[PDB]
Image: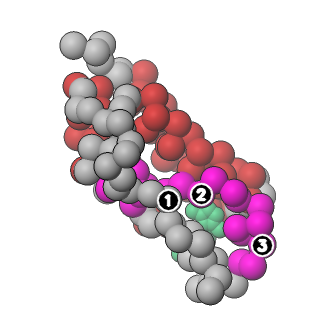
Amino acid sequence: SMNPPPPETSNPNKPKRQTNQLQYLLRVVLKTLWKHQFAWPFQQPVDAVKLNLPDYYKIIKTPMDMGTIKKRLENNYYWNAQECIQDFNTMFTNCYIYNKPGDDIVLMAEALEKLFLQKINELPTEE
Ligand SMILES: Cc1noc(C)c1-c1ccc2c(c1)[C@H](c1ccccc1)N(C)C2=O
C-alpha cells in the first residue's frame, strides 16, 4: 500500500555457497557495524510511510539495508563476497543520493562506511 516489499532474502533458485570471505563478512564486518551507536537507522528497510517520505521509493530504486544484509548472510544467500560488498555499497550510496551532505543520517552513514572500508581492506584471501 506504500512501502515496497523488502529485497529478497531467500530463493532456492539463487546460487549460493559458503566461503571464508562471506563468513568474515558476517562475523567481523556486519557484527562490527551492527553494534555501532549510529547503526539503528540502517538495521531495517527505510519505512517511508512512518517517515512521511513519499519520494523515497521514487528516488531509491534499489533499496538496501543492514537487516536485509544480515538475513542474506545468515541464510547463506550469497555466491561471493563481492555480492555482499555490493549490498553495503548500495546502502551507503542510497543514503548519500537521498539525503543532503551534513544531514545527521549522512554523518551517521559516513561513520559506518569508514568502518566498513577498514574491515574490507583486511578481507582475507579466499582459502
Ligand atoms: C537510512 C536512511 N537513508 O535515508 C533515510 C531517510 C534513512 C532513514 C532511515 C530510518 C530513519 C531515518 C532515516 C530517521 C533519521 C533521521 C535523522 C537521523 C537519524 C535517523 N529516523 C528517525 C529513522 O528511524
Separation of residues labelled 1 and 2 (CA atoms): 7 Å
Does the magenta portion include 1?
no
Q: Residues within 10 Å of mark 2 (few under 14, many from 20)?
A: many
Q: Amino acid at mark 2?
A: Pro
> Helix, strand or loop at disc 2?
loop
Over which residues does the magenta segment extend?
53-71
Mark 1 and 2 residues: CB-CB less than 8 Å, in contact? yes
Q: Which residue is mark 3?
A: 55
Q: Amino acid at mark 3?
A: Asp
> Helix, strand or loop at disc 3?
loop
Left or right position of 12 against 49: left
Q: Position of residue 119 (x, y in %)?
A: 38, 30
Q: Nearer the viewer, residue 41 or 37?
A: 41
Q: Which residue is mark 2?
A: 63
Q: Nearer the viewer, residue 104 or 64?
A: 64
N-terminal-most mark, 1 or 2: 1
Q: Residue at 29% across / 26% down in the picture?
A: 21
Position of 19 relative to 109 (above/below): above
Q: Amino acid at mark 1?
A: Pro
The quadrant of the rendering that contains the N terminus is: bottom right
Q: Residue at 27% across / 44% down in the picture?
A: 76
Checking the image for residue 7, the label placed there is 1
In the image, ligand 1 is in what quadrant?
bottom right
Separation of residues labelled 3 and 1 (CA atoms): 18 Å
Mark 3 and 2 residues: CB-CB less than 8 Å, in contact? no
Does the magenta portion include 55?
yes
